[PDB]
Image (cartoon, chains in turn brown, cyan):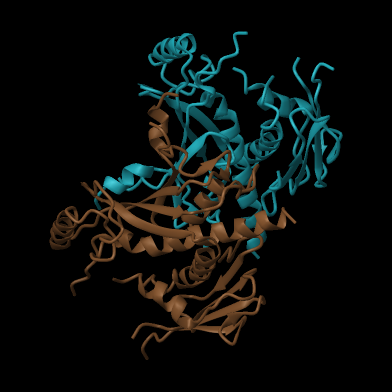
Length: 279
Length: 279
């Protein structure tokens, strides 16, 4: 069955089987006055693969602007008279709304890149490189090596795991709600909704275990005592390997847009909670 | 300090400052008929230290048994007309309740051990050893090395990180609520309430990124598609270094009881949700 809702103030509630008639979300809490259209949501949906099933805004937008009421989303499944991009669509469409709002309001920029596929690691990050290749890889000299590895596993009936880093930049200080709703805790919660995820870490993450107590190197990954620092938010996740020519070697790279979406959803929620706690 | 509640059906709500008058919790959802007394809670409280302040049960127990009504817990702070074990007390007391219930009902066994302090790692696990030393260490040949490392770092005035593994055994299959309240997701959420945690992983965890695709080797750590497998639940967390003879080189080992508590709280919650969902 389902726990089909996430968030306290920015709340997303969903339903829909991948094989069922369609998929739906109700998104609460988005302030009035955000420019929004179907296109703004499709753009992020269509980033899962880099004419597919089209999202429709059913409510909450009048004359191209959010009204402040609950926003209803629908995808009608054109299953032609079990691909799990349909299981991820409402999350990504809803994250898109949170992204667009956080970008306009604060200039928050949320972006993910694959740092590792199996035994190949990316060693350096160039944000202009991540859309040029189909791995979301920021290291233009690792792309060939990732491609060779994918070519290699495709041949031999196997698949590999991955590790993604997601960053949220320009996030105001103060967001998060200790004891139980720390920003890191809700992040980890949200990331762990993505299917093959086996770990989440913030900042230096598991390395920390072997550390001893570098200037402003953001060891905390932008969260301290469960509340945003002001620094960039760094989150990493590890996705496990996944079970005609099915061209399936590393599905985990295609999780980048949804990990971006989940981080946006959590930040949007905590934005609103922080605001509610300040008037 | 607004997020003072956790759980949907097994719900724990807390309050209290460390130099306020006292600390409180209200714990909802525990069925009637569990044998329970202050002592059962103190035992777990006093495990934070491998004269002192005593938890009191205010409601929800009659003639030594839970009634099924909300259980109120109080600790009056005897400040003596400087320790942070106070902000962790209500979580551990309440986890103790979830623990006892899950042990009597299903024989569930939730235990944690420190696998790593800084540059020292434990190899072997012997549950009998873990209470014999003050590191919750399961390797009797590592205890000396952990003691040496810690003795040094206190005299040097340096702190080190740690890594804990928490296991939940004999957990029934079926528990957890995808999409957004998967068991692993609520585990991670809960573990990250513990201050100093920078990562949570389930099963093989971050190793998974470097893997390629008997089966009963818990690669998944007892959770598959966000729901319990029947296998042992394996969770690891990494705690960062902190910063008269009260210098805390690795305060992270003392997190073992609270990580046990948090895992108990989440399991208890998902037990009840699972029960509610079956008609």
